[PDB]
Amino acid sequence: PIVKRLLGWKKGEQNGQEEKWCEKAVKSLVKKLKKTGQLDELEKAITTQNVNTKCITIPRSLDGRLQVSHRKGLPHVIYCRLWRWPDLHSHHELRAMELCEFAFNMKKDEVCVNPYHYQRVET
Amino acid sequence: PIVKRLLGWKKGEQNGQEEKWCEKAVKSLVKKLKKTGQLDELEKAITTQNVNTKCITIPRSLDGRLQVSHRKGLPHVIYCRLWRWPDLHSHHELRAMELCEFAFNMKKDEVCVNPYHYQRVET
DNA sequence: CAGTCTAGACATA
DNA sequence: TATGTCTAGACTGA
Image (tube, rainbow over all chains, first blue to last red; front, side):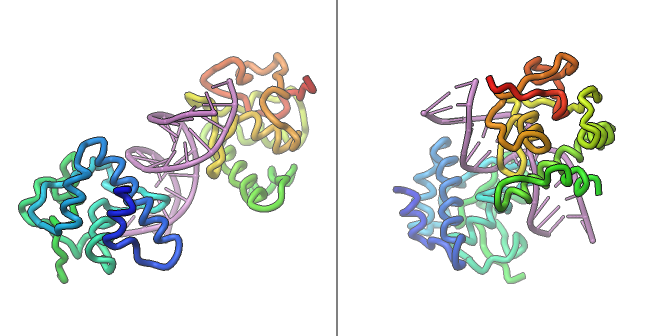
């Protein structure tokens, strides 16, 4: 369904339990977005690659990490790495685009995980 | 240390990840008991097998289950099975000894996990 | 800066 | 009842 499709745009790089984990990671995002009705703005953004899409938002946690499968990480890094930069090392190689209100660095209650609202800085 | 020792009195039956699990299971118990100074009454009860030892208590949870390693279970069953009856199927083949105030069935804030305050009923 | 652990939250059966 | 799965929050570090 939506998951298999979204996965289509860069299933998951790394040999092994990684493809399965990438699937789990898409599943979490999709489950949460359904609840808030943003699954389609996600669908648009990944496919059309339109930087000026609405902010696809997920709730933040005290420490700001997200756990999928076992694996703990920053929301926006997990997804920019999934659909844009599989090379992405950390949240330092990233920076929002002013047009993102909930751009993580703003410590808001929601976090924009729309991969097209961040640009990768080579520092 | 204390864990390697207490483990000694029935390390852990089942082939495999079990022996490692039984070790995790004793580590949980020992960690909690240290915080409340009951590790020695545990030490005494397991070694001396004295039924009339103090009630070794662990805090109960809403559902009353305890999770060790992944594996969910009832406190008193996981421990009676560890140093008494490895055959123990469920919490029905068990019953307190009147002398245990926090004998689980009493739905108190604490749960007596002293394996020598329960007796196995063959129903 | 990051890896482990588990009660409590679900969601059935 | 009874039971399995998933993770935010806590804890542990070095």
